[PDB]
Length: 51
Length: 94
Length: 71
Length: 71
Image 1 (cartoon, chains in turn red, cyan, orange, purple):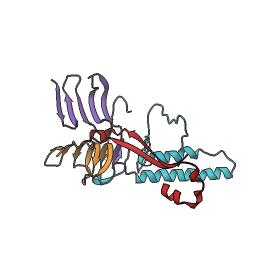
Image 2 (cartoon, helix red, strand yellow):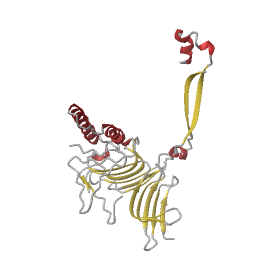
Image 3 (cartoon, rainbow over the protein chains, first blue to last red):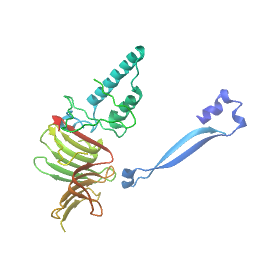
Image 4 (cartoon, each protein chain N blue to C red):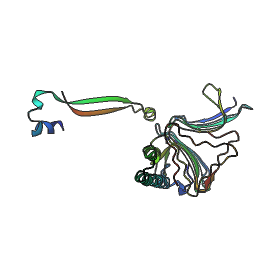
């Protein structure tokens, strides 16, 4: 969607005046069951951000 | 807690198709009567919380208690009985 | 194979699945549908999860009698 | 002494305490918190009494399903 927005003619002139990135987040998941299986888990969220 | 048969344990642990029909049907009745109360300028019941209860109890997506029995439930005691909702409504649908 | 079973010819079972993260205990008898107490990662005959937690299960009656109170 | 345990490597256990006057049975699996059925003189890890009677116990769902009725 970030590449779509850089292609998007709607924001054609707005984006060059700020920073268009993909923010990535990752927090720890408490899953006690998967811990016993040796599987530690993370929740990764990503969106297109504009500063 | 269910008096519904799941023969030979064929099905999910929490198959509550008839419990869900009972919840859907009660909220459906509560909601039609809430429209009737507005048309009649009566005080309206709390559909909001009975609507979350359907959400919570359906497949027990929130830690609630669903008692279903296809042939009737009796809650009897020689002593006092209390049905109490601490922060929300009690709904007796029939 | 991570699954201990005490099984009798009448298919009275005490099965303990040791598969880590998917452990369960099944206590099952054939009488009354299947009268079972399933604990943990409850799987069906296909070993597909049919529920997590404790299931007291029967096609007959269930009686839960506590002489001092039920919580 | 006074404890017969059928404990599997996944800590699915059938523990039977024979201490007279303090007998209990613990059927516990690790899945879902500790999904246990505790019967009798129920004690904690410190062997201190935490309850008397039957406890069907889980951190997941409980399902009690009797096709002919629940009492």
